[PDB]
Image (cartoon, rainbow over all chains, first blue to last red; front, side, top):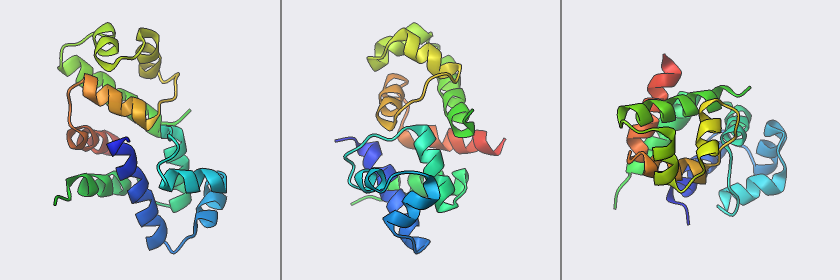
Length: 78
Length: 76
């Protein structure tokens, strides 16, 4: 698997739930396909930086807060 | 033209120079093509998370340190 990929998709899912959105909601807000979002949270697709940027825009989260959460996630141990 | 992508490739170049590596060096260390590295640094290639992970491994930088630098860059 890709370790980093699983951390990124974890944080996408986490913010999604915090915002109270479904996968369809995120698809709609991103201009992305439902299956692609579904696939990303399943880690069964690779994700470009441009798609990530479309996802952050769909989530309505700033770059900084997103990466700050990623760091927190990468650090959580045991 | 993608803002985030330009920030990412900026930090790749920055760390590359800090480590004293040429693009060929990075290509060799990443198992990526010269042209791909070259393209990434001019913002003319899109890059997946897996490629980014290959790149960080070639630069011998940890995930945290890389994204810490990315945040710094974005806030500049």
